Structures are given as C-alpha cells and as structure tokens.
Amino acid sequence: GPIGIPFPDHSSDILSGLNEQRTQGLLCDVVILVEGREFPTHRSVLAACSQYFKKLFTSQNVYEIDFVSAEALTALMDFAYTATLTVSTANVGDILSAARLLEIPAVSHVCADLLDR
Amino acid sequence: GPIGIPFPDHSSDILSGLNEQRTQGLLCDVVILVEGREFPTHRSVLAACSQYFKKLFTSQNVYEIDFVSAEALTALMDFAYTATLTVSTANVGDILSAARLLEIPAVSHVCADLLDR
C-alpha cells in the first residue's frame, strides 16, 4: 500500500533556499522600490504572505510602494523569508501600520496584541 | 528592541500558499511536461528543492522532462510543495532514480533504504 514519509525540516529548507535567492538576486521575478531601496523578491512568496500583494499580482518588473517605510518593509520581508520578526518598541507602531496596509495577519495580530489595551 | 520574535509554523504557511498557487495554476511561471501531462510550477521552488533544476534555471516557459516518469514527477512535486513523500513497493525504485537525476538528496536516501530492505 502507500507509505507516507514526512520530512520535518523540508519547509524550513525550502524557505531558506528562497531567502538565498533574494539575497543573491537569483530567480527573483519582481523588485519592490521603497524610499530608493530595491527589494528583489518573488511575487509567489509575497502573495502567500500578504493579501495586498496577492490582489496586486492576480489583477511590470518594478513596483514602487509609497505607503510604508523602507524600515518597515525590510522587517516585513525578512519575516516573510526567514520566519523571524525583528522589532523594537520604537518601530512597532510603524511595523503594525505597514502589516495592516499590506494585510499580513501573523504580524498585524502579534503587534496589536503587544499594544492592546 | 531590536528583538527577534520567531514564528515556528510560518515556513509551513508559506509552503501551503505556494501549494494552493500550484494546485490552481495561479502565479506559476513555468510548465513541466511529462508523458503529455502538464504540471504548472514555480522555478524558484523547484531550484530550492532540486540541484538539477537550480542549474537548469540559472544557466523557455515550457520544459519536457523525458528522463523521469509521470508517476515519479507527481510524487516528487507533491513532496516539494507538501513536505510528505508518498511511495509504494511498486514505485520506489522509480522515485529513487528520479531523485538521483534531479539531485534531491533527502529523498534518495530514504528511498534507497526502503528499496534495499
């Protein structure tokens, strides 16, 4: 009969490979531009993470985003590609604003819970 | 801050979204053709998963892959996008030869051991 063989580290290894690709600018199909900083990424990974980008890409190589800061987009990209959110009580309000406009629920829920109320 | 908050299930969330994309033919940038069967996929994900595909995509939009069976490619694509490989007594040597040619070392190790037993 069929045997299922699970691979515990597989999804981490796939994400690590996609992160290596943006870091080298290899096989990226899109560039986001925010405050003069370029972010080579994958439209597929952005859409799996952000309902804003999913909507944008399912209806250019370059997309200029004006409604978030470069600092916040950097935190949010690093999270999408590495699974770790780097944040301070100085920039958490900025990260939360951006996560709410880009519609990234994991981030927007954790940031708002830190600040609730 | 700065403080690195880990999200332990994020990598599986990303892969789940990539798998939904593939299952529907959405945001897929390449088609693999094997025995008249069409598999819409992402070259970034295949390269992250297979050293053969990494070299191929970093060296068209449709590729006919004649050196693996449709049965073996189906199993290996499901693996790439889900983290579980499903095999049987009857198809294990076939998945083992495809994993060696596609340079997917994690799969060939498990399959070799299954076959030798």
Image (tube, coloured by chain):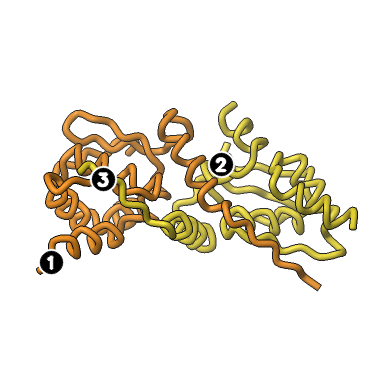
Chain colours: A orange, B yellow
**Residue beneath disc 1:** A116
Image quadrant where residue B86 sits: bottom right
**Residue beneath disc 3:** B3
Q: Residue furthest top?
A: B59
Q: Quadrant of the C terminus of chain B?
A: bottom right
Q: Tell me the distance, in whole angstroms, between the alpha carbons under discs 1 and 2.
A: 39 Å
Q: Earlier in the sequence, mark 3 or mark 2?
A: 3
Classify B61 as above or below A6.
above
Instruction: Judge depth for marks 1 and 2 and give the one in front.
Output: 1
Q: Amino acid at mark 3?
A: Ile
**Residue beneath disc 2:** B48
Q: Tell me the distance, in whole angstroms, between the alpha carbons under discs 1 and 3.
A: 19 Å
Residue A99 at what x, y percent from top left?
A: 22, 54
Mark 3 and mark 2 on one chain: yes
- Give left or right: position of B57 versus A98: right
Residue drawn at (35%, 55%), measured in percent from left and top? A49
Residue B112 at what x, y percent from top left?
A: 83, 50
Q: The residue tagged with tag 2: helix, strand or loop?
A: helix
Mark 1 and mark 2 on one chain: no
- Give left or right: position of B110 versus A50: right
Residue B11 at what x, y percent from top left?
A: 45, 54
Residue A59 makes an appearance in the image:
no
Residue drawn at (59%, 26%), measured in percent from left and top? B59
Q: Chain of mark 2?
A: B
Instruction: Judge depth for marks 3 and 2 and give the one in front.
Output: 3
Q: Chain of mark 1?
A: A
Classify A65 as above or below B75.
above
Residue drawn at (13%, 66%), measured in percent from left and top? A116
